[PDB]
Image (cartoon, grey):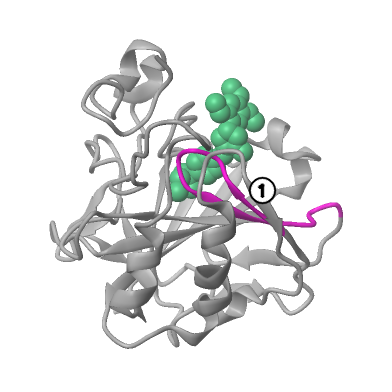
């Protein structure tokens, strides 16, 4: 009876095995655009992905992860709210059964069709497992997806999903350029929060881009053909793998822009 997104093991159950689910800095949150304060002391954001080394794509039963070589500073996030250097280790998405839901963060309670998370760890803790034990251990760059025009930089991901349909399947995924997933603008919102899946650790500086990317209905339909289940188990479509908005509590969301 491990955690997931069903009625019997979904986000309302997680607190039973992971009590930090009801903690003070849980993610995601609703971003109230009229309450978020422009902070003129936020430095520009530095996304330096030109030397990024992608290796593998994995269906982990909750999402699919595109994994990077993080054994050196190759693909890093710096600046904005961050001190020091955060190494890209993986990206993944959360998405819905229909275009009206799927994002984890919301903007004035608006839900996007999906949300991309680019996950980075703070190099001053040496490895990822050490970083997630620290309040400033991770930086996740969150990017909303809306359904419209195709994202060309996403199609190599979409076309490999048939090969990793079920939990525990992986495929070689070299020479993938994550810069193809970014919007034009790096304007963002930032707040301190958590992992959005168990173990829900309160180790994340969230950086959520204001500008969504557009993907096509055909691209997101292929996300929805993935399976949560292992091969030769009953088919459960991988849809609605998003946690809903958590209480903001004693936190302030900061805007990079006026
Ligand atoms: C208790 O120790 C661990 C358990 C554990 O899973 C049960 C894990 C898992 C969780 C991991 N990471 C992760 C989860 C959510 C996000 S999101 N959606 O962007 O907020 C980003 C990263 C990971 O790599 O692995 C990591 C752990 O330690 C490193
Ligand atoms: Zn995520």
- Residue under the point 75% across and 70% down: 52
Task: Give residue 46's position: percent from left, percent from top.
Answer: 62, 74
Q: Quadrant of the C terminus?
A: bottom left
Q: Is mark 1 within 8 Å of ligand 1?
A: no
- Residue under the point 86% across and 57% down: 72
Which residue is more in the foreground, 163 or 28?
Answer: 163
> Residue at the front extreme?
232
Is residue 173 in sight in this rendering? yes
> Residue at the top extreme?
16
Instruction: Say above or below: 190 vs 45.
Output: above
Which residue is more in the foreground, 45 or 95?
Answer: 95
Is 164 positioned to the left or the right of 253 in the image? right
Ligand 1 position by quadrant? top right
Task: Give residue 11's position: percent from left, percent from top.
Answer: 28, 29
- Residue under the point 78% across and 67% down: 53
Q: Which residue in the structure is indicated by mark 1?
A: 121
Residue 54: name its quadrant: bottom right
Which residue is more in the foreground, 257 or 216?
Answer: 216
Q: Quadrant of the N terminus?
A: top left
Residue 211: name its quadrant: bottom left
Is residue 39 in sight in this rendering? no
Which span of residues is magenta-colored? 56-71
Task: Give residue 229's position: percent from left, percent from top.
Answer: 45, 35
Instruction: Say above or below: 109 vs 38.
Output: above
Is 36 positioned to the left or the right of 153 in the image? left
Task: Give residue 67's position: percent from left, percent from top.
Answer: 68, 55
């Amino acid at each position: 009876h491990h955690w997931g997104y069903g009625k019997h093991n979904g986000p309302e159950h997680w607190h039973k095995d992971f009590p930090i689910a009801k903690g003070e800095r849980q993610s995601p949150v609703d971003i109230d655009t009229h309450t978020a304060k422009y902070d003129p002391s936020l430095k520009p954001l530095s996304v330096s992905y030109d030397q990024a080394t992608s290796l593998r794509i994995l269906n982990n039963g909750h999402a699919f992860n595109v994994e990077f070589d993080d054994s050196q500073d190759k693909a890093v996030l710096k600046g904005g709210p961050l001190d020091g250097t955060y190494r890209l280790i993986q990206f993944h998405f959360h998405w819905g059964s229909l275009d009206g839901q799927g994002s984890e963060h919301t903007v004035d309670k608006k839900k996007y069709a999906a949300e991309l998370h680019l996950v980075h760890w703070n190099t001053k803790y040496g490895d990822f497992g050490k970083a997630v034990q620290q309040p400033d251990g991770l930086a996740v760059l969150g990017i909303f997806l809306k359904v419209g025009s195709a994202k060309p930089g996403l199609q190599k991901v979409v076309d490999v999903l048939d090969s990793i349909k079920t939990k525990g399947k992986s495929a070689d995924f070299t020479n993938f350029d994550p810069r193809g997933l970014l919007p034009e603008s790096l304007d963002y919102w930032t707040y301190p929060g958590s992992l959005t899946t168990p173990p829900l650790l309160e180790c994340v500086t969230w950086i959520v881009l204001k500008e969504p990317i557009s993907v096509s209905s055909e691209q997101v339909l292929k996300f929805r053909k993935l399976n949560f289940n292992g091969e030769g188990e009953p088919e459960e479509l991988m849809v609605d793998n998003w946690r809903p908005a958590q209480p903001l509590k004693n936190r302030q969301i900061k805007a990079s822009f006026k």
